[PDB]
Every structure is written in structure tokens, then in C-alpha cells.
Amino acid sequence: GAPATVAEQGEDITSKKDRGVLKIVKRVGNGEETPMIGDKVYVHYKGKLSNGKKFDSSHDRNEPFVFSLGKGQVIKAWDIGVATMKKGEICHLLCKPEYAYGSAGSLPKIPSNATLFFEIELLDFKG
Image (cartoon, rainbow, N blue to C red; front, top):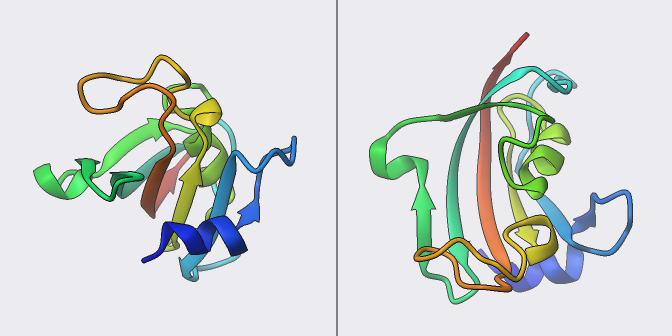
């Protein structure tokens, strides 16, 4: 639910504390278990524009999005967000354009200066 709640109540998980990435845990992850930079991460996810319209989802293909954590292969908010996640955890990220696609956007999906809302589930990670 509610991007306005992530805004009001979320945790600022940026080192800068500029509120560019804000998080709320929706399901508590298992172990106190998290990837490190370089680990292979498998996520399921949904991306909404702040008009609620969904621009991209791993549930459309039914295919986990896989990547190397911490290597800039994804937007900054994901390298950041996912590094704070435990295995099995679902969270909600409100992300400022600064940590997403800036004032360039990623057309045609994402217009310029867009605040993005993600639901990311960390399914698994490997070394």
C-alpha cells in the first residue's frame, strides 16, 4: 500500500540522509542473512510510477531479476535497498530520481525526474 506511508515513516537508508531511498519492511527476512557486494542476488519485484501505474514487474515474465550486488548494474536505490535486505524479506522502497533515473529518465517507461516505488522480494543470494 501507500507510498505516502513510506514517505512519512520509512527508514532513510542513504549514507547522506537526504531521504532519497526510504524503506519499510513488509515481510521479515530469514536468518539475520544478507548478501555482500559482489554476491549474486535473485529478486522478485514490482515498479510503480508515483501515479500508481506499473512500469515494470518480474511477475510479467514470471522471471526473477538477477544481478551482482554493489556493482552499479542496477539503479542506486537497488544496490542500496537490496544490501539492507535479509533473505526471504519483502520491502517497499520509495526512491528519489537522484538514486533512480535522475532528470534524464528512462523513456518510454520512466519520464524525467521520476520518483519510483518498488516492492522487492529477495528470494536468494549466492557467493
